[PDB]
């Protein structure tokens, strides 16, 4: 059925990480599908420090309708999916932020 | 108190009324009690039940009323969603509170009208056979057994067979 | 047309309490009536409450042993009978008191489906 | 407090006949009667409420009537899907008492 | 039936009433008929027309009420628009249905009040000249020609010139 | 005019009424004037004040009701915001105008009911001591000083001590 | 102030039917009246309906030959006269029955503009 | 059923005069009268409804009156823009009958 | 519970006008009453208006010299006394006329706080 | 127009005593009385309105009463936080007249 | 009056189409106006197949 696909792109905090990890700079990520054909070109050389981590990462996602076909073109700075999902839509819900514990009723 | 029966010319209620709303107190020779008026209270209870259930059921049901969340760049979207949620809540509060108040008033004068209509019903059935007093009570001129109550609460109070007795008691001397 | 969904089937030893639900489909404030279908015997109304008065009326041969409570919040009627005994083996039917001409009181309108409550060893 | 004495106790008939079920009450209950048919092994369900009105989704062959201490239920004709026991309820005053049960069975 | 005239002490309506609502039935010697009460029914029809037309016209008119469409990336926008449309529809359904029901009740007891006010109007005009009976009917003690109707429906029923005749008929022996 | 007292059987109002609403005009021997009925007008003023203040205060207050602005690429957002603002305004206009009209009617027949209830209150206090006339006025059979007014507006009009005088004046010859 | 826009001008042979509209500007439930302006003669009310009663009243010399229908959905009054004849040549005026003191019945209030209906050869 | 006999049939006057138009009815129509002026070649339009009230947007020079079988319409003064025929309508009972027409023309 | 915030403290020469406000917290249509607390003397009600009648009633020894106006738009009562004199030195208290049982008239309910108005040299 | 004569003029007492304040009126004011305590140097505030009702947030030790031309205010017991002057108001007819003032002071 | 303008950019499914059709890669499209000055740089080398 209509599956959901998750992935990300890693932005190292300097050119050194790019050069020493993916072995070449100017690495693009181009996911393509029937209705999703945008490209990512992550090339950044500095960041602040958050959670004891300089570099940053952008988590994208998409949706695959029945019979569709998604193709991942990349040569660096890619976070390939490792467990995709399989949704069934369902409309009318939303997140509740709460600390109370679970029970049955 | 639009019709002015309850808290009007019937000063106080009765604590012993437990079976029905618009009862009686027949302090006749054979005994006493607080026998209800089954037709009127049944119709009244039916009416209030229709009112309350219409208030409940007409409210349609949908699976969400939750404002979504937005990050620090959709302050337009967050303020718009807050405006929609707050305007819906404001309209609902105004409408619901003005309803609650308005049909609270309608319920009060509907009970007032039920006591009223009952009072004029008994008065029309009795005409001048029984004189009126304060508090919405009555005073039968004729001798009056339990069959009175049978005829009064079934509406079949035949005036003529008790007419002349009342005519005698009008002056009694 | 309120789809009444009563509880399941259960059995208990004599001299205990019972819990039979009358979970409705939509919020409603009409009266509630409960009736016993003992095998071979006819219907007889045990108890009931009116959400208008709020008082809980009962049969003059049953009061005390049986209590009925139905929170207006959920409109779900509860069925409690203390000191169960064997001859009370029956199936239980719950009425929501709602005909076509609005919610009228003194009638039964729609009915439940039945909950098997048999008291034995 | 008021007993609903069904009369006759039990008779039998065929498809398309004339049958009358009489409900007798000691005290006058005005016109707050009912008429329940109870299929064997099924949930009971009413036919006539307030002794005159007709429940929605019911064949018009059933016609109640009477008031006070004498009531009736005049079936226009019998079909093979309405053979059961019949009960009459009083609701003029509590407690609510049902009836005995008048069964109709294939002649 | 708040005032308890229609379906109260006037048990049933009249099928022959075709010209007006709150008519009469003068079973007098010269003839009969169902002549309406032109003033009261005209005022009542005026009132219901104001009620209905106010319900229509107060509803403002704008050129769109259509929810727009959104692609697969504005699920926030689509859900928000659905929430606005569904909340507007829910508020409109609740308000419109509670209105329809509430002023249905107001229309019923307004017709009840019209029949009532007419009944006490005739009763006050007649005082004790004509005795009252059930069903809201009347019984003139005096001989009563068509000029009665002229005076009754124009409100100019002069009591004194028919007073003594009724006084004689009070006992008649 | 549901109860039919104001503009019903009380044809016109009084210009000299300045202290209270539901006054009197005691054209008795000792003098005259337009002394108000303090209890009834005080209760009525209380009721209208509750009505108006409930209309004001139940309306909740929030710090913005302003539609935001959008550039030439958020025509969806601008049209949606216009739809929300216009729908809120339309609902508010319909609700507010239907309210204003509906409790205008409730205020009119509430004043009607106050004059009514006062009229039947005085009529019940007087029973047949004072005959009724048009315009809601009255005619005391007995000699009637200012103490009448004291008893009438305090509700303590004891019938028996003036009963026989009225009985004499019933025929007077 | 309801801007009544009646139909255009039309002519037809004797012994046929006619269709004159009274399309209003806003939804309204006040009564409808139709009047004939024959050249040289005075006004005379032919027929009319009240959307409250719903009955269609008519002049006692015209009933049958003329029918009036005005669907409450569009509040547009229709004008039909069967068996047209020559002396019915006139201009037709439609009244919406609405004065300043609300919609009052028994008056004319605002009026139409006129539809030329001449029956000749 | 009731005929509206206009009286006088037709007179003439000048600017700023005293004119009275009387509408006579066989049967009493209470006070549900009207007063229509009809400009030649123009849509008719009323002046006084219910025989006493004044239509909005009308000069106060027109004052109706009378009730029962005798009515009136008292123009305070004549101006050159209100010269036409005049009709009186009854609406107490159906059918609704108009009048004959009283024209006023330059003297 | 309407938090009445009256004006500040001010002094003026004899034979002039005074302006003491009774700015409330929320929109309200209950009556307004003003009372004088002259040192050593008791309370006495001077004037007041009812937003229902709209008329401005006054004490029979004060009328003319004192006027009260309270625009319904802001529900803020204004206090004007012409021709001030020395013995009118006092502190002024404003009442909003609202008890627990709704807005009732003929009572005082909640009160103001006080505005020092002393007339001297 | 009606004078509110407080009686007694002024007495003294201690904590937990029996004191009665009587308000006398020339003309009958029905039951539209009030009872204001006025702390020295503080905003006045009422205790009993309509001569029977009790203001919210007030100790129940105060109980008003009486109607017509004779009224009363029966304090159940005295505490050190309710020592002040007392006034009675009439509102049956305008003008609204306050009272003289009955102070209570430490014995 | 206020006219509307329409245009598009073609993304070939490989570098071969770019090289053999526009004769040079890294081709930009820069529409500019008073309040519309964004640039398009379509350079993609693969797609799925839709509508042949």
Image (cartoon, coloured by chain):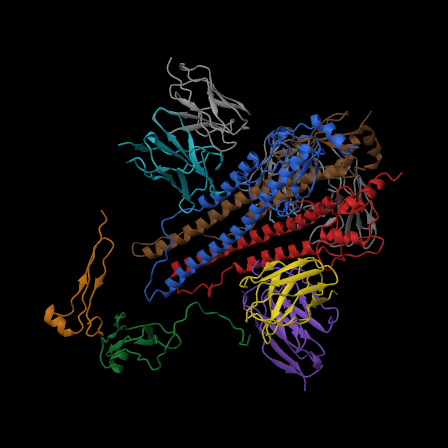
Chain colours: A green, B red, C purple, D yellow, E blue, F brown, G cyan, K orange
The residue that appears at 26% across and 32% down in the rendered structure is G121
Work out which residue is located at the far bottom of the displayed protein and give it: C121
Front residue (pair E6, B168) = B168
Work out which residue is located at the far right of the displayed protein and give it: B173
> Which quadrant of the figure contains the N terminus of chain G?
top left
Could you tell me if residue F21 is visible in this image?
A: no
Front residue (pair D41, F101) = D41
Can you give x and y, in whole percent of width and height, for residue C55 in the image? 69, 63
The residue that appears at 40% across and 25% down in the rendered structure is G42
Could you tell me if residue B4 is visible in this image?
A: yes
Can you give x and y, in whole percent of width and height, for residue G78 in the image? 38, 41
Front residue (pair G59, B12) = G59
Total number of numbered labels? Answer: 0
Occupied quadrant, residue A60: bottom left
Q: Is residue A63 left or right of residue K21?
A: right
Q: Is residue F146 left or right of residue B89?
A: right
The residue that appears at 35% across and 56% down in the rendered structure is F77
Can you give x and y, in whole percent of width and height, for residue B117 in the image? 68, 47
Above or below, comparing residue A21 to residue B61 in the picture: below
Above or below, comparing residue E87 to residue B131 in the picture: below
Front residue (pair B39, G120) = G120
Can you give x and y, in whole percent of width and height, for residue A44 in the image? 28, 72
């Amino acid at each position: 059925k209509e599956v959901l696909v998750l992935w990300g792109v890693h932005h190292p905090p300097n050119i050194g990480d790019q050069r020493a990890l993916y072995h070449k700079e100017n690495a693009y990520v181009s996911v393509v599908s029937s209705h999703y054909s945008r490209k990512f070109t992550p090339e950044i050389a500095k960041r602040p420090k958050v959670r004891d981590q300089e570099g940053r990462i952008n988590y994208y996602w998409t949706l695959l309708e029945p019979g569709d076909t998604i193709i991942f073109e990349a040569n660096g700075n890619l976070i390939a999916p490792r467990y995709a999902f399989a949704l069934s839509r369902g409309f009318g819900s939303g997140i509740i932020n709460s600390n109370a514990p679970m029970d049955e009723c | 108190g639009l019709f002015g029966a309850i808290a009007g010319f019937i000063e106080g209620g009765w604590t012993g009324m437990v079976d029905g709303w618009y009862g009686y107190h027949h302090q006749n020779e054979q005994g006493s009690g607080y026998a209800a008026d089954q037709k009127s209270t049944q119709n009244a209870i039916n009416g209030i039940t229709n009112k309350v259930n219409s208030v409940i059921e007409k409210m349609n049901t949908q699976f969400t009323a939750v404002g979504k969340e937005f990050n620090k760049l959709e302050r337009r979207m967050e303020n718009l969603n807050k405006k929609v949620d707050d305007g819906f809540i404001d309209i609902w509060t105004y409408n619901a509170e003005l309803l609650v108040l308005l049909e609270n008033e309608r319920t009060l004068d509907f009970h007032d009208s039920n006591v009223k209509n009952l009072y004029e019903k008994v008065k029309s059935q009795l005409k001048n056979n029984a004189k009126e007093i304060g508090n919405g009570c009555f005073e039968f001129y004729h001798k009056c057994n339990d069959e009175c109550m049978e005829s009064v609460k079934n509406g079949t109070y035949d005036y003529p067979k008790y007419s002349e007795e009342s005519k005698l008691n009008r002056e009694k001397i | 047309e309120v789809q009444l969904v009563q509880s399941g089937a259960e059995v208990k030893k004599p001299g205990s309490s019972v819990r039979v639900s009358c979970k409705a489909s939509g919020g409603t404030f009409s009266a509630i009536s409960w009736v016993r279908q003992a095998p071979g015997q006819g219907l007889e109304w045990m108890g009931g409450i009116i959400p208008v008065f709020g008082t809980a009326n009962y049969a003059q041969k049953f009061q005390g042993r049986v209590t009925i409570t139905a929170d207006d919040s959920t409109s779900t009627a509860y069925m409690e009978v203390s000191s169960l005994r064997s001859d009370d083996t029956a199936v239980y039917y719950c009425a929501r008191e709602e005909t076509w001409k609005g919610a009228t009181i003194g009638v039964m309108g729609i009915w439940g489906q039945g909950t098997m409550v048999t008291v034995s060893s | 407090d008021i007993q609903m004495t069904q009369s006759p106790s039990s008779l039998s008939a065929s498809v398309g006949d004339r049958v009358t079920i009489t409900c007798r009450a000691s005290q006058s209950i005005s016109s707050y009667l009912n008429w329940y048919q109870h299929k064997p092994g099924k949930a009971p369900k009413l036919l006539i409420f307030t002794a005159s009105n007709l429940q929605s989704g019911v064949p018009s062959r059933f016609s109640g009537g009477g008031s006070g201490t004498d009531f009736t239920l005049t079936i226009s004709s019998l079909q093979p899907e309405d053979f059961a026991t019949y009960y009459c309820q009083q609701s003029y005053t509590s407690p609510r008492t049902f009836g005995q049960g008048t069964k109709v069975e294939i002649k």
